[PDB]
Length: 164
Image (cartoon, rainbow, N blue to C red; front, side):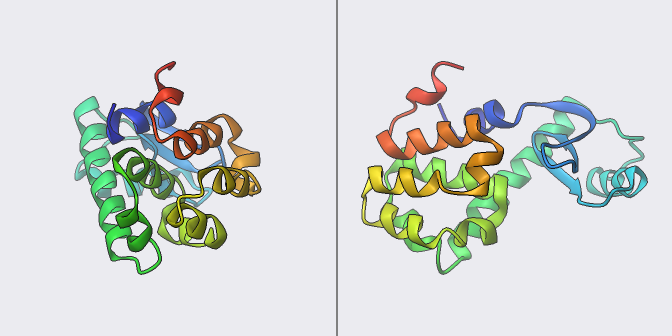
């Protein structure tokens, strides 16, 4: 299991513009297009992102390209962020993927806000950190995904995804 497979499980693949869990216009593998209520705004962002007139629809290849970009941008974001970098550097391979999953979903800024949890992961207090992470809007809103993530940090293995 790797970061792409893991995110492909959590986000799904959709080749037509759709609304995410929060109501935002999204495409492919969790690629947010716009927070704007306008489907047109969305289709506009899409064409700009793909470089073609897509009329709200993309190909598998195009979804994967956006996916490649997104994951890269997530890793680079972590590496450039003063709060995240040290956490990431302190973690093992599996847990690093897990942090990436969070950043892909909620953005750098969003994860960097989880001060206490970050500190606990840094300290390798797995159980404590799992309980702290569970006390969030994130968890309450997407509990099945959050639980997979939390369990992954908890055990440091891919069991939660070997199911799926």
